[PDB]
Length: 606
Ligand SMILES: O=C(c1ccc(OC[C@H]2CCCN2)cc1)c1ccc(-c2ccsc2)cc1
Ligand SMILES: [Yb+3]
Ligand SMILES: [Zn+2]
Image (cartoon, rainbow, N blue to C red; front, side, top):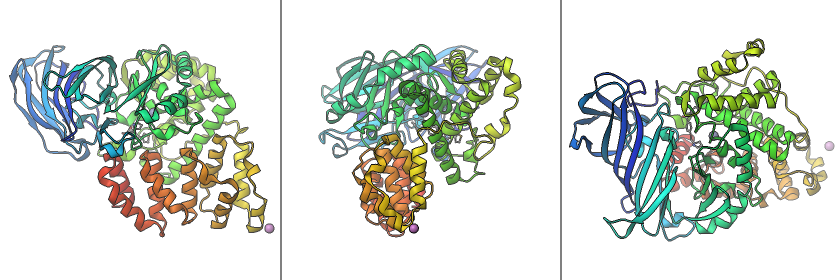
């Protein structure tokens, strides 16, 4: 069972369907309406059940056309408050009923960011977006907020008529709102069973442009053209993903480019991937994020982690597929380059947390841990490393991709644990069980720190990055003159980024070295968010005061946590910028995404 949920477990009852009828009130920052849950008993004589909620106001609960008794328990910190509903008639096993709950969200809902007009591109209209993963769906509506339950859904959403609503679902029409002519009702259908963390909503002044046979890009009008170019490889990537994973079952694959405070690189919402506008580099160089979100259409959205302890199943396999997509497009040496970079990121995470820290285990125990606090690259990169190691052990990528496809087929529409995965691995590779038994499973799955074995990586594309980084680290003052813009002439953006990542692993460097780097390479002029991020961290860690305003700007003008959190941390650690970093956070806190505001405050000890 799921230690992050207060709701009745799947062994007691299962939600089969949600019909959501709601209205988005920008004046009050509330979503109001009804959640009708079709629930199937899994027990004889079922007389009550419990749902998760968080900062919800419940008006009433109706079953069979009458109000029923319910009770909200005391809040359990980040888990919210359990809601026990008294059923009017005891249910037999497999019996289904509909429970219609009237509710309103709180402006402080941790699932939602409410943006004022000034926080958008267009400056006229407000904007709302959700981000339920991992356990914030309970802050939008009452539900069994666990990925161990999958349900279909329909929705009707009333919004101001000048705005557009989109959900993780197929669009199913729009009409004027009969209860309020100033509004429109948008309708949605999701016919494929999903865990509730994949329920998503955006409302704003959105426009669309077609970019492939099954893909529209959506954004505010100011970003449509750039977005359409940036993500033009989307259909090519979908075709490759279908080859690797099997049929794409979700109908459409649309993309939504959010405002800059979107807290993550991407979210794999079914039918409508959400992405950060920090991907808009102008050259398609950050497209691996789209490859990642596409890949979730199989690993994560079809085969799902049963509880958050098993999150690496979602991410390790998705990164594995992501990197195969990149390798098919740009070659096997590039796959290895990205694989090796990911090991680098894993090294960073382990050093950050500490080599014995419980959040560096592959399988974690989130009992009494806020999921958002555990979140890091570990499940992505330790998960990927395990799969890449297994690929090498078991006879290579063609063989291992055969496993991947069979795994997706086996567990489609289900929620599974690490033991389910391992059992299937052993079944699929039964003729190589001797090889599988050579793996130190206890260390790989359950021990903290770096894995016991590092995979073999082709170094072809990495060599020049390491060599340049080593030149800088070993340079003395009299060597600085030798550096020149020609040093970079054969490096791709990816390689520039890796040179910075290598160098940042040894930071600080002497301030004179960093000043020379700007003199000869002009990294200040690079707008690629990944490069600028690493460059500004290197500058701040090396105590360059000139970089303070640049790093503060980047930290606040966008909100992707990958960048905002370490920039604020670095600025707080630099004595010269410490006080300004704290003031800047205090001043921005009220208008930050709620999860981002929480995590930055924790990082800064404020
Ligand atoms: O709860 C989450 C969790 C929290 C947020 C989340 O999603 C947030 C964003 C990420 C991208 C889109 N949604 C997903 C899982 C979680 C679960 C496991 C781990 C972990 C650590 C070492 S091995 C496994 C870390 C975190
Ligand atoms: Yb010298
Ligand atoms: Zn992912």
